[PDB]
Image (cartoon, coloured by chain):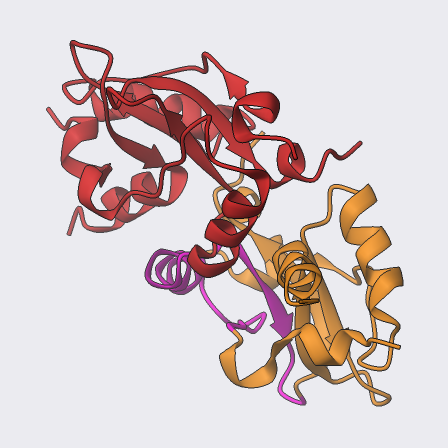
Chain colours: A orange, B red
Amino acid sequence: VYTVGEFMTKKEDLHVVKPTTTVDEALELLVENRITGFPVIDEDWKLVGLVSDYDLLALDGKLVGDLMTPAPLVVEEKTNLEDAAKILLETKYRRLPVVDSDGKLVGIITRGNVVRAALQIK
Amino acid sequence: VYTVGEFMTKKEDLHVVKPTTTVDEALELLVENRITGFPVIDEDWKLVGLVSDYDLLALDGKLVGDLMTPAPLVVEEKTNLEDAAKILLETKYRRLPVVDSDGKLVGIITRGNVVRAALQIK
């Protein structure tokens, strides 16, 4: 079987922030890195939240920790890719953080990554 | 005043498709270019539609033209940036195509671009 860990955006090529990151640091990070959000880690690289441009710009002196959406839906590396694919493909979710046994964030799987996986079946 | 044309993603750095583009070509383009959609142009570089991953993967032998969302909300280059900013910041829209007098697509303004603009005010 395929796993999320094989197709995920690995830890090396990630963009993360901490709850100590300022809204301006995060806005900067988004602008440079052409992303619309990041996973949010504590000092132990544990996953404590997710944050997006909508959250940053209060849409509808403050820090990511203030505006982040904490405790999100999560997958594992050994997680069968097809389950991840179901979620990605049947919900508003375009990303899912991948964490390990110790709750430590080790990647992210996007609907893109799933698409790429589908395509590289050849 | 500021205009959209000053801060938009210009025509050079664009990614477009045509209605003749196949779903697989578009899926490829998305995977390489890390985008979640494109503007859709005819041969005259006129804007005829918009298309996204959700449309591509029929979510909820075919071509973009079949699945594209045509005739979307549009801005101009001389369009005062702040109006664009209002739309971007008060709606589900993260992108807006920029076209000229002849209806020809000459760029796109994203909420990102607006953010970058806000930041480079310094």
Q: Position of residue A16 (x, y in %)?
A: 54, 73
Looking at the rendering, which quadrant does residue B97 occupy?
top left
Question: Which of the 4 quarters of the picture holds residue B57?
Answer: top right
- Magenta region, residue range: A15-44
Asked if the magenta segment contains residue A24, the reply would be yes
Q: Is residue A97 left or right of residue B65?
A: right
Percent from the top left, x then y, of residue B110?
Answer: 37, 37
Q: Quick one: A12 or A66, which is closer to the camera?
A: A12
Query: In the rendered image, which quarter contains the C terminus of chain A?
Result: bottom right
Position of residue A40 relative to residue B88, above or below, is below
Task: Identify which residue is drawn at 64% across, 31% down.
Answer: B62
Q: Position of residue B70 (x, y in %)?
A: 50, 15
Q: Based on the displayed image, in which of its 4 quarters is residue B61 positioned?
A: top right
The residue that appears at 35% across and 56% down in the rendered structure is: A31
Q: Is residue A95 left or right of residue B33?
A: right
Measured as percent of width and height from the top left, residue A82 is found at 86, 62
- On the question of residue B36 being in view, the answer is no
